[PDB]
Length: 211
Ligand SMILES: [Cl-]
Ligand SMILES: [Mg+2]
Image (cartoon, rainbow, N blue to C red):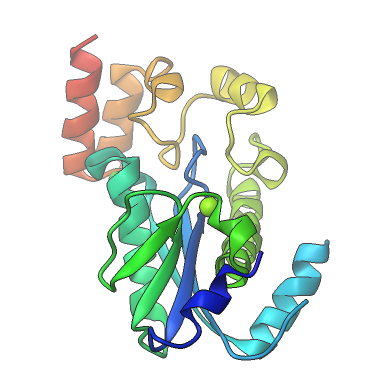
């Protein structure tokens, strides 16, 4: 909509920040931070290629473990800050998709920022394309799960897969739909095998015990 134009001149280097995967049942939250010089007008992958040519980009991830330990809001912020740390240029100001998120660099959050700002639009594209590739990797690791299709979102098929095959360490064990399927025995298996940390094990065992 052109909101970036307001921030072009008084705010030093400005980056746009967005995420992919906040709403998922499995996998990380992936954040992108983007500083664009040049003008930019699977249209996603078309745009990714132009972004790659015309922007400085940084990527930050927060794992299922971190989501389970810190909560989805803190984990998303952790990813976003990591994305800013990953940028080769240090921005002076950030435009962030959402509401009430305070990052390591001062900024402003825009509700539906991905429709209002080109910078944030560009960050949303990078984060989505890159997270989608990762989820396709996870279908290779866990072929009983169609992560390549649902991307770990709680679709009918994903839920059917969890019910039939069991929860995985890459599931967000603290989220009700997963937590309600998880057994004490499977959780102990994960810990026994070194598939989850002791901190994560204890956290989820508490959540399960209080049920
Ligand atoms: Cl873990
Ligand atoms: Mg967003």
